[PDB]
Length: 50
Length: 50
Image (cartoon, rainbow over all chains, first blue to last red; front, side, top):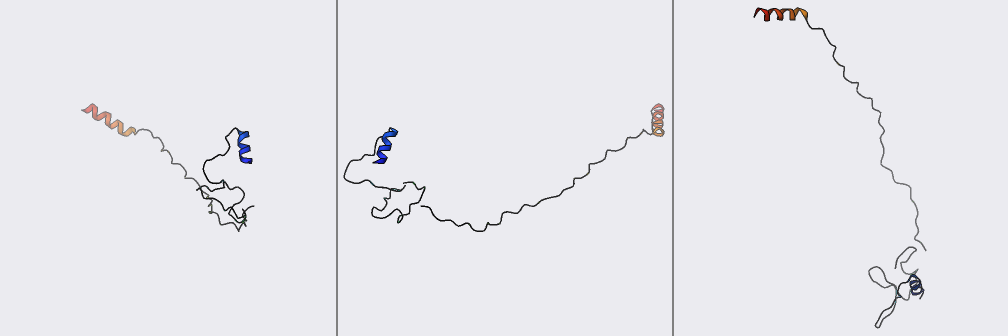
């Protein structure tokens, strides 16, 4: 929601897709992060990109 | 959150070598000389004799 809100202020179209599925965070190779574990459990630190 | 980092004792840098150098003294020009009169006197006689 905040990303879509920021995009509209920048004049960019919000995130949208079609078909059955869900929205989630992924790595540069497309691998999705774990939905049930903490970012402290995952290998994420300050300055990372997702 | 950030990854921890402990700095060890610094590794040895590549050693610089100073150098004291004294230059070679230049070469000396030869001394001029006066033509040999008791030779040219001979030559002017020979060509006259010819």
